[PDB]
Image 1 (cartoon, rainbow, N blue to C red):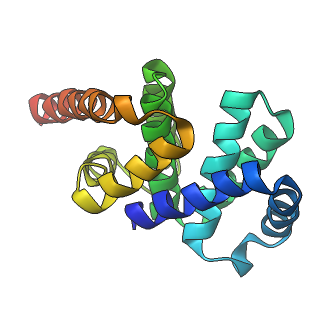
Image 2 (image 1 turned 135 degrees about the horizontal axis):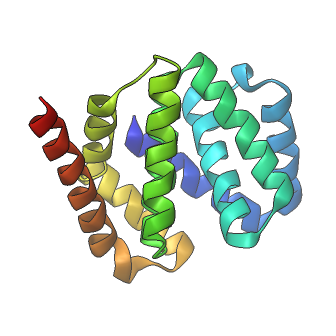
Length: 173
């Protein structure tokens, strides 16, 4: 579930801050054998690593997130899509709307080119961000990121992004 990925992303991000050595050891473990961990855990580690890459300029986290994302795309496309939507929400939360939309577009393009997902999957996944269970966890992410004042406007921007996509989908039929 989307909200479980968010909840677990809170735990990964707090671990990176509060015990970086245990963060590094568990990431090495997931990179060595991601299939030994639950899909939610792999997706959350991907998101935390992608956030470290983008927000701290962490080259190793960047390459590690790329490997985990690739693995999720190849083996569990629905979890891949959830991971990308959560990453997009967090970038939007941080005020990086262009980056958030590029993440969604990359996710869409990888999913369709692999014949594992489509525009309707993306729309459905984005809208799961707005449910209460997911909103509670994004509030937790926002506490982690000192971005509480931007939760609503970030989700509103994503909703209009999804709305325009859905309208083009409708017009195209």
